[PDB]
Image: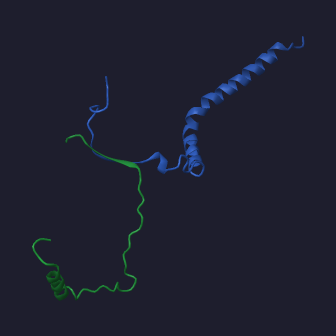
């Protein structure tokens, strides 16, 4: 973002980032899952503060 | 008079608690409760029982003695 033109950035990216692998080797595909929420309390008592 | 906030000084203690809707009210009410009750009863029975056993013995002896006294004797 700033003073630039889109095609120049695209060409530079094609030059300097074409070596990255993006095949998702084997089933090594980390996918998130739903997270359980819990109503609860946590209390750290430090009366000196 | 006494109110929460400066009743005493406490430091370096962490407390974890869980909401009442996230947990059971009767987790192990029979599997674990009965052994604990047996433990407490075994602890307390030797302290509590012998006085009442002695009272029972005195009660029986006194009642039998009174009943024997009331009945008449020969001669």
User: Which residue extends farthest right?
Assistant: B75
Q: Is residue B36 visible?
A: yes
Colour theme: by chain
The residue lying toward the viewer, choosing from B44 and B20, is B20
What residue sits 87% from the left and 14% below the top? B73
Residue A44 lies, with reference to residue A9, above or below; the image says above
User: Which residue extends farthest left?
Assistant: A3
What residue sits 68% from the left and 23% below the top? B58
Please state the horizontal and vertical placement of residue A25, each as a whole percent of the image. 35, 86
Q: Is residue B16 visible?
A: no
Q: Quadrant of the N terminus of chain A?
A: bottom left
Please state the horizontal and vertical placement of residue B42, each as a whole percent of the image. 57, 42
Residue A21 lies, with reference to residue A3, above or below; the image says below
**B22 displayed left or right of B2:** right
Residue B72 lies, with reference to residue A23, above or below; the image says above
Q: Quadrant of the C terminus of chain A?
A: top left
Chain A: drawing colour? green
Please state the horizontal and vertical placement of residue B36, each as a whole percent of the image. 55, 46
**Number of residue marks:** 0
The residue lying toward the viewer, choosing from A10 and B11, is A10
The residue lying toward the viewer, choosing from B72 and B74, is B72
**A8 displayed left or right of B19:** left
What residue sits 76% from the left and 19% below the top? B65
Which image quadrant is residue B69 in? top right
What residue sits 47% from the left and 46% below the top? B20
User: Which residue extends farthest top?
Assistant: B75
Chain B: drawing colour? blue
**A12 displayed left or right of B1:** left
């Amino acid at each position: 973002a700033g003073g630039l033109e889109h095609r120049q950035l695209l060409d530079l990216a094609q030059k300097h980032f074409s070596g990255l692998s993006g095949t998702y080797d084997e089933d090594a595909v980390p996918t998130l899952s739903p997270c359980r929420f819990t109503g609860s309390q946590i209390c750290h008592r430090e009366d000196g503060l | 008079g006494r109110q929460f906030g400066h009743l005493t000084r406490v430091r370096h203690v962490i407390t974890y608690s869980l909401s009442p809707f996230e947990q059971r009210a009767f987790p192990h009410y029979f599997s674990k409760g009965i052994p604990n009750v047996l433990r407490r009863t075994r602890a307390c029975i030797l302290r509590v029982a012998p006085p009442f056993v002695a009272f029972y013995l005195v009660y029986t002896w006194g009642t039998q003695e009174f009943e024997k006294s009331k009945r008449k004797n020969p001669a």
